[PDB]
Image (tube, helix red, strand yellow):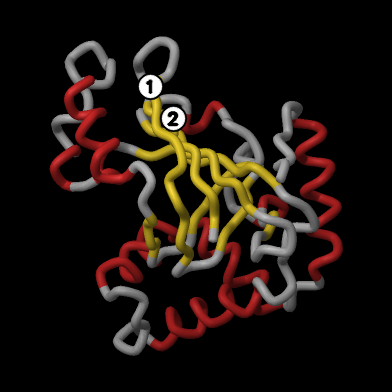
Amino acid sequence: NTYQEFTNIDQAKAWGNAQYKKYGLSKSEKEAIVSYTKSASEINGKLRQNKGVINGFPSNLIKQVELLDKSFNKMKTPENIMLFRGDDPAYLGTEFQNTLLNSNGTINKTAFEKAKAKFLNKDRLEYGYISTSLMNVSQFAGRPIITKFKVAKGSKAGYIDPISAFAGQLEMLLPRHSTYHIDDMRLSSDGKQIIITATMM
């Protein structure tokens, strides 16, 4: 199957804005999504720390998590689509935090091989929500790891950009507790990034 890759910002914004108009998110769901864009590091951190169990969270955060989860009943992609994410070295593991990059900002080729052994052709489970973009935006251009997610028609996926507190990210949110499979891992032309291709489940 083939996955729509947006190659133009205006095309992407237009498609996304059209999807957002159809969602019919409630007042509470919108409020929860706005807050997510302000506090995503905290929310996703707590979900990872607790392996998806929200029972011990403060009551306002439980409600927020439930409203985000519920939002995806209304937010599905109408087609196969490619989504993009940038990540820092710790995404690969604690062992990559101060080893993935040499002093030139170029990927250490030995660390790259270890990352390939750890992850290539394997599934990964993410306890947090996954913030992505419809394109490889300049925002995460400093980042050493770029992942391209292949997300199938009908999958839970929401263009939340219109109500995000921040600009320029063409942001598509994926639900928490998602699994994806790493199909391909390779160094970029200039050796400064690892490009990962993954299929969302």
Check disc 1 and give the amino acid type: Leu
Task: Look at 48% across and 64% down and name the residue there.
Answer: 178
Question: Toward the viewer: 65 or 150?
Answer: 150
Q: Position of residue 62 (x, y in %)?
A: 44, 84
Which one is earlier in the sequence, the residue at label 2 or at label 1? Answer: 1
Vertical side of 186 occupied by 57: above or below: below
2 and 1 marks in contact (CB < 8 Å): yes
Q: Position of residue 13 (x, y in %)?
A: 77, 40
Q: How many labels does the image show?
A: 2
Q: Helix, strand, or loop for circle 1?
A: strand
Task: Look at 27% across and 75% down and name the residue there.
Answer: 50
Classify 10 Å Cα crowding around label 2: few (below 14), some (14-19), many (20 and above).
Answer: some
Classify the position of the C terminus by image quarter. bottom right
Vertical side of 167 occupied by 103: above or below: above
- Residues under labels 2 and 1: Cα distance? 6 Å
Vertical side of 100 occupied by 192: above or below: above
Task: Look at 86% across and 52% down and name the residue there.
Answer: 18
Question: Toward the viewer: 39 or 110?
Answer: 110
Classify the position of the N terminus by image quarter. top right
Q: Where is residue 45 in the image (x, y as percent from the top left)?
A: 32, 63
Check disc 2 and give the amino acid type: Ile
Q: Which mark is residue 187?
A: 1
Classify 10 Å Cα crowding around label 1: few (below 14), some (14-19), many (20 and above).
Answer: some
Q: Where is residue 93 in the image (x, y as percent from the top left)?
A: 21, 47
Task: Look at 44% across and 69% down and name the residue there.
Answer: 177
Question: Toward the viewer: 57 or 135?
Answer: 135
Q: Mark 2 points at which residue?
A: 195
Q: Residue 1 carries which label?
A: none
Q: Helix, strand, or loop for circle 2?
A: strand
